[PDB]
Length: 48
Length: 48
Image (cartoon, rainbow over all chains, first blue to last red; front, side):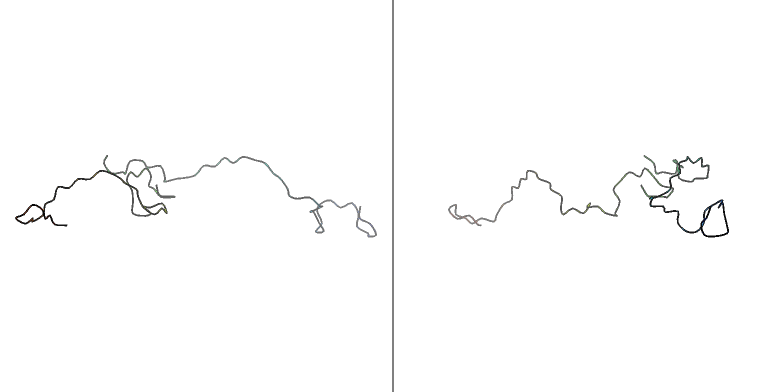
């Protein structure tokens, strides 16, 4: 509920302030990345 | 090694920075020398 207005029961974030006197937002996770790499060709080296 | 390059495990000192930001290289050791002089006929007079 907003006050002194006609719109009521906000469902979501307005554009006023999410800072709220706090510092950050934290999200945890783990990647699973598959890609192509050229940096493990260990044969083209000089003799001895 | 060279970063982000298909190149690794190089053996041998390159010409990039052979001094590590230092000043000199301390090497000590013995030394011998048996040189001669065109001395005169007499014996009391050597040459400096």
